[PDB]
Length: 329
Image (cartoon, rainbow, N blue to C red; front, side, top):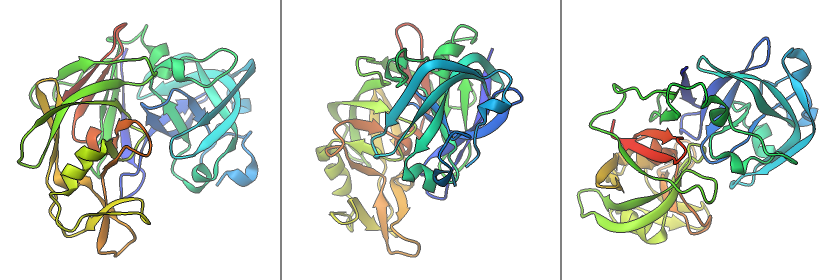
């Protein structure tokens, strides 16, 4: 089997992408944030505290295929400080025509204010390794893990758009969705993430610096977070750019034409266009814009978030020894 689903930016800034997910029988369609940086499929629900719901909810008592996973609970906290917790059902989940039965669907009893405040996200669908799932006492498998037995190939691909719709595919590689060839690189699962080591970077039309950058491919992080020295080298090429303590990162004039940023994948190179690094004005009508490449020093891990991933066709190869592929597009 295969599946293919359209993913859409939630807002004009590409803060996140939502993908429809059908849960239950009959299907309840929720728009979830597909997150290669976590491993829980959780949803706003009829169980969620009413004052914390503003979203479409999953009602397990309306699904004939929902089963309570007795004694199971979950609680998750994300790098941006958001969190949620609740109980666990197994149910039928379909994405883009690919159906998994017995998928754990984590029903929120409570959600943090950032989730309440975001009307467009009805929950998350984690796609990191199942060792990061937060269900206790027994962790639950991700949608991808449960799908692998049936898939035509144990792969999924992310093709995120710059201010445009894109695609998540499960089970096949669309050879028309990218240019050139895919270069694959090794993945470490020691921390549960799609963790890999970039071979280096270049700023604009300058030289490629061979420097190992260990980081994670995370569709659920907005920006590209890289080592401080790398980020400084980038913004040194932008004459109005400065770090702003009060805004919380590099800011620059919206009218600047920004240089590209290139990262290495083995011998191959992925070029992020300068426009992708303009994340947008700090407020509507401001002359100042927030940068899409920021230092990872404060969060302690390098993250190839959406600013980077949307410049590539990305293959998440979930064979027993996983690998990560990138192609230009």
